[PDB]
Image (cartoon, coloured by chain):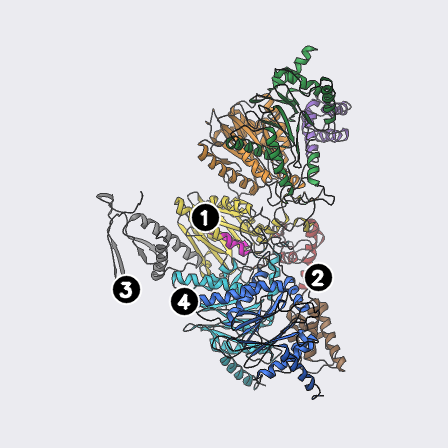
Chain colours: A brown, B green, C red, E yellow, F cyan, G purple, H blue, I orange
Amino acid sequence: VEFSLPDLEGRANIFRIHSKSMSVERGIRWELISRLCPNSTGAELRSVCTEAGMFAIRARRKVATEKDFLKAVDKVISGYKK
Amino acid sequence: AGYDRHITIFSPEGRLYQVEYAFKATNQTNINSLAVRGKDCTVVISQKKVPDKLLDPTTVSYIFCISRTIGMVVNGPIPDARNAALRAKAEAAEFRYKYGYDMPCDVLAKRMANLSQIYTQRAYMRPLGVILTFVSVDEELGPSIYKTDPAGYYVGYKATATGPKQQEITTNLENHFKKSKIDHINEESWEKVVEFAITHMIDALGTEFSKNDLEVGVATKDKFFTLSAENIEERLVAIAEQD
Amino acid sequence: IHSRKMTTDDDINWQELARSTDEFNGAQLKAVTVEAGMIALRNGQSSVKHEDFVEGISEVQARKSKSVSFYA
Amino acid sequence: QFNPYGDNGGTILGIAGEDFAVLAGDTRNITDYSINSRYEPKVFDCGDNIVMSANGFAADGDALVKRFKNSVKWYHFDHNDKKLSINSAARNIQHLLYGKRF
Amino acid sequence: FRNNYDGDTVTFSPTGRLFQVEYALEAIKQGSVTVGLRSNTHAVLVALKRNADELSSYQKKIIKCDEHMGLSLAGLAPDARVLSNYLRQQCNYSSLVFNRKLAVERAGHLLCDKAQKNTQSYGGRPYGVGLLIIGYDKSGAHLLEFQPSGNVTELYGTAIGARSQGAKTYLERTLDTFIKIDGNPDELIKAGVEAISQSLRDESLTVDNLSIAIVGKDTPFTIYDGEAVAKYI
Amino acid sequence: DRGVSTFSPEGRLFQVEYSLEAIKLGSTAIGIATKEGVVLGVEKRATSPLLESDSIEKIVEIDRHIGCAMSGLTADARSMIEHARTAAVTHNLYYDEDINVESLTQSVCDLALRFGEGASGEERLMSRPFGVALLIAGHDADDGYQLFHAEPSGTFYRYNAKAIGSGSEGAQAELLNEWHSSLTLKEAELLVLKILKQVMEEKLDENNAQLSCITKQDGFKIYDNEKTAELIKELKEKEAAES
Amino acid sequence: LPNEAGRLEIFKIHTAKVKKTGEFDFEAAVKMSDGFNGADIRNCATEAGFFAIRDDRDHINPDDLMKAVRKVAEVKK
Amino acid sequence: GYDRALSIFSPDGHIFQVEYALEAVKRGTCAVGVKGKNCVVLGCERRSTLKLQDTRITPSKVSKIDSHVVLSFSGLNADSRILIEKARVEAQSHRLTLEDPVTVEYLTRYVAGVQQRYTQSGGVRPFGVSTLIAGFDPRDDEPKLYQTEPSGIYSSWSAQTIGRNSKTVREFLEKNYDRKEPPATVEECVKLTVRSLLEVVQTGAKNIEITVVKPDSDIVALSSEEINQYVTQIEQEKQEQQ
Amino acid sequence: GTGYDLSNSVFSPDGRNFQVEYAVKAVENGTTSIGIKCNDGVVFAVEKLITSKLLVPQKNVKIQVVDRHIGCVYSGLIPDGRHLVNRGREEAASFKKLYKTPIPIPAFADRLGQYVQAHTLYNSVRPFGVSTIFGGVDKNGAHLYMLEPSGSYWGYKGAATGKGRQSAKAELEKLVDHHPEGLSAREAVKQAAKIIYLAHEDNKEKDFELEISWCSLSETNGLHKFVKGDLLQEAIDFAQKEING
């Protein structure tokens, strides 16, 4: 059974799924978030939603924004490299 | 670099693993040799065996005639022996054109040693395993024996042996030469020279060997010849004619 | 031997399937029978046709599986 | 000493017309007063509506032609059987001719 | 270990040949199914062309080397081209030097030698591509199988690519019949299409995947390409 | 380092696989070939006041009938262009006419094979393969308007439309729905802008996008900043009136 | 490693307790080895015997013995 | 043969050797170029800590590539000579052959090209240097500023900064320049350049070397005396904005 | 031990490099081929494996000619054997031009020997994994030689190599003893065919097709020619008569 590398359509679904439970303020398209991943594993995806929430809590927020999700992709992938 | 025995470079200890292993297990190929000097000949006896009845033992060669006058006795395997033979033969011939003169044992020995050394430093070649004993009866020195060994080391002998009955051969000749006060025996005919050789051989290796189990190469002034099978039995029977 | 134990539609040709599998071992021919049944399980069939087995081979048996036809 | 270069005669005539063109040539091949051939095609079809004749000295004709025949073949392979244009073929010859002049 | 003998192409291993070489034989099966068949007067090549997409256009699985010769590839593309150029070069020179077309046999043996040289060279590699090379020379009709380690076999019929064993069962039965039809192109051609669709078992056949090439006693290298293969199914 | 002749159990070389990894990290290049032209569009990206954003573009002209847009490493695409210009120039001199886009891709792909230690088949002078993939678009008088995707692996396929880059998975999917066989040059360019807007996390300006076109009365023609912006101006209003 | 002499003695000794048709030429058998000590020689004996269980007999030919020593040599050193 | 590998792929689609080349530049000294719309200013560090250097034969950071073109760098001097030499030859090659003064774009392509080669080609490694190339095209009064990396990539930039604390100097510069209103007068564009480069050199007003390039071969290096004066002034400005 | 399994550019303590051992092994992993010296000639025969009816007779004969009077047959892997021979050929053409005489069988042994030995001094060239049995008639008598993959070679009276090496030496050693060396060249085809039959008994998973060739100075006149027709056909019968099954 694979748990290696999923598709663009696939990355989108796993993002959509962790952020339901969260409050959010509008302007999110999952597709856009997915786009910034050149290659991921399931571990990385879980890290994008949870990290995106943290930028909001520092500013003191309950909601998540399109900006936050982008910011979390950039951090996670780059650390994974090397 | 790499490592010290995956490519040829110095060991931790300043040794070379490849030359020492080249000394050892290239004489254990069911080969034992001796060379002794005549008065006006040079004699070599060397073992040479054929394990099939289906292997023509004529082609089986480990005394080679390098030129019409020069012989080279190889201790070690036929893949190696022909790399050294090709070099020897070429060197012999080249020498003959260029310098106008027949090739001495010593010059050939020295040239081959230096070449092996270069191949020892190379990281994409090996030193050959073979031990090469070059024989003739030079008109510039008399009967001669010069031996090279695999490390790029070489040195002249008056009588030599190889294979682990080295001690036995040496001691019998040493005691003999200390008594007679000479390192060459005196006798004209080649026949009596081969009988002297056999005497020391039989005692020392503790056995006698068949015609096809021996190969005897004789150096004479301006000829080197190998003795036919009947000719090698004639000699073994001739000492036993005495008995 | 495999096809006694379990239902089949009694049309399945071992020789033909055998040409279709390359470098299969005995245990792996037994795992194809299981996968042929997993097709069958999804399909709502209680037996296996030839097709059902062909599809079984395509899926993993985990040591060798004949399905190669990709390259553009 | 040596110069193989001479002459072998023959005559060719090319006429461009309204939709058509001819390459007419005699079939006599000589070296001096001796007859080398009394039929030997002196117009030859290289393919692609291109017919060709190298009149003069034979020895150069044969060479010029062989270099060019392999170019017709290589043009096809390397460009998926796209047929050779009269103008393009003319440029290709120019380069051949110019390639030996030593 | 695997990793111990894999790194350069100059090592043998206890198996009798290098691991990498087996991986080159494996690649052929990945690439396209091509069947080869002959009678004794003509020889027929049938090949399935694959592309990647709807809006992709096919990659050619027949490369014509001469007006009496061509070959099919199966496996790695980039090597199949480097080989087809070499064969072009070999062909032409034969014609320039010897006035000679280049026999299938003659070509196979030159190609083999080139293959040994690139499997003793350490930076070099097996090609990773097998080829079915067809011709009609003055040796008769021919099919040869080339493998990228230098294995060259002359055959009546064979297949490389997807379920080779698949096609081989078909051919071996219908063999005795079709090969004694000597002087009728169409039958041998019709047997080729009948075969190739039964090797398939996770693909289907269609007109513009299929492409047929025949060479023979009265057929100079001719491809039926796209539409015109319908009339051989 | 890493083998240059060492394949996977499938038989796909490490170096090829690694080639595929650099490609996926560039900015999208999208081509649609139509019946009146080929459109090639790129996302140039980056907007800064410390950046000259309209002095850099990713659509470079090879010839008066051939362009290429790239995606992947840009430094690598310079060696590919130097080889490609030389080959096209030498063919225009010999036969006076246009070189075929498929023909060009094969000539380039031949020199993509060198990397590593040499062969005895080939002299391998480089160290890695090229880490850029290209969409080469052109015109020829014998197949009209065409679009080609060259992979650095060796494979080159003709397409009617293809996208490459990071955002290609989405992009291609859109291309198919929008694609039909009565599509024209003017529609295709508008549509390119739609695709580009959708996938951006920004506003589409001509300092993050560049258009280009092919018409056969002018060859390969760059759709200039001034025209591309006028097209962007028209987009924003019309889209923002469907909402 | 044995002698030629050592191999002969041990072949003769092993086939003495054994039941056989025909006088055996141990001398060939020795050639067909190259340095087999007593344990290796025993495997050759039983090997011959296997074709004799099949040939439905408690005796063995010269013919069996030549084949037998060679098959054991090939399957190892 | 030493045409075999010495630069290999990453699994991430980078190259190991290019990632390591950029690190040497960062540890290094800082060079900057800021544009007016009349000049292009280049600042280069000379932070002599020790006083036992004799500084008329201590290497400079400013090279002529051509009489209207300069190259500045941050990185290993040893590698930079090798690049600097090939770039002078290329300016003279054009001059000889085209009968024409050199255009900035082609030179940049050339500088990019040797570095690009050495990543691609085997038994060589890329240089340890990033550069800034600037100058003016012939019969042209608008400034030109290019950046090249030892990856071999290249770009134009309105202003760019390299070496140690590149972040800090970009970030600052961004607040003090607009493309719509860049500076007209030499004095104020130089004031800004000296002020950015003060903030990273620490103490420096003889350790900062300014060279201001106006159109077509008016290239003039401002001196210590002049620089000390702008630093005084900056110490007056910082208590007018308090 | 180690380094000697990947290289040949350094020397084993065993006196025998592990890579060299692997080369011999692939020889025994081929087919049987043999060679018979006789009182005027040499006769060569090989077992050609039949797997399928998709293979064609006498185009996948493993007998390949060099010069005019040397026939060369092998056991091991096909590509190694053909490349080795193609090199023999080239040296043979060179020989003929230069010395205006055909290439000897002893000369050819040396030519092959030096190409193999060269690849066993270098780790940068990989050697051959075939044993090639060859021979002919020349100006200086009849010769049978066998080349082994170390770069060891000698002249033999009889030779075998391959899967069926043992069974072949047995059947040969009886026939050679009985005769002075192998009697006539005619007789030798019949004898050969018996040897192949015994050698088949180690295969038995494939059928075989018998292929013989000869080089004879009394019934071919010094040329290498195939043995086919009547002579091959009497030989199949002789084998099947005495050898039963």
Q: Quadrant of residue D22?
A: bottom left
**Circle number at residue D19:** 3
Q: Amino acid at mark 1?
A: Gln
Q: Amino acid at mark 3?
A: Asp
Residue contact between numbered discs 1 and 3, judged by CB atoms under 8 Å: no
**Distance from the alpha carbon under mark 2 to that under mark 3:** 71 Å
Residue I113 horizontal/vertical position (percent): 57, 35
Of discs 4 and 2, which sits in the foreground?
Answer: 4
**Circle number at residue F141:** 4
The verdict on a common chain for dots 2 and 3 is no
- SS label for mark 2: loop
Crowding at dot 1, Cα within 10 Å, few <14 / some 14-19 / many 20+, comes out as some
- Mark 1 sits on what residue? E90
Q: Chain of mark 4?
A: F
The verdict on a common chain for dots 2 and 1 is no
- Mark 2 sits on what residue? A1
Residue G72 horizontal/vertical position (percent): 70, 33
First to last magenta residue range? E70-83
Residue contact between numbered discs 4 and 1, judged by CB atoms under 8 Å: no
Residue contact between numbered discs 2 and 1, judged by CB atoms under 8 Å: no
**Distance from the alpha carbon under mark 4 to that under mark 2:** 52 Å
Give E206 or E149, whichever is nearer the viewer.
E149
Residue contact between numbered discs 4 and 2, judged by CB atoms under 8 Å: no
Query: Does A68 sit left or right of I172 as displayed?
Result: right
